Image (cartoon, rainbow, N blue to C red; front, side, top):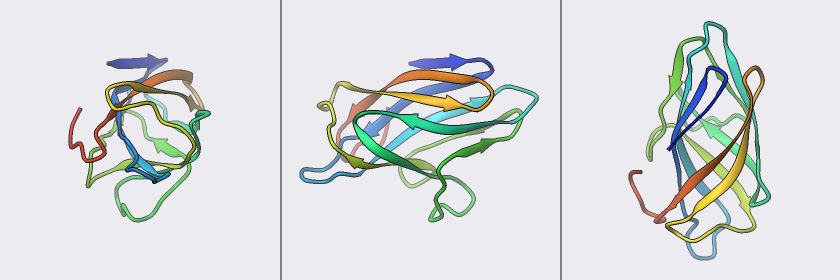
Length: 125
């Protein structure tokens, strides 16, 4: 599933469902900036959770609340690598469903995605 707005593409967003009793989960998506100018992912809007923390290379233990995207760049995400932490989850659809959220890019604007809800220990897709 690809989403696109402006020169931004978001490929195959998916998340690990939170473990029973837990309120955090990891989300993974390929973000591509095909513009000759930088962009910034500055917000993730959802009624499902309070906030997000981006963990991106280099220094994956450090977090940030936006992602600066250089021109002609991408962020690849997977378990053990770059990822988004969804923080203070109040509700999440079942495994096999999707979670609706809106991404806000400073230049490209807003796109609503449906991130696939995968098993809590899923490694792909």
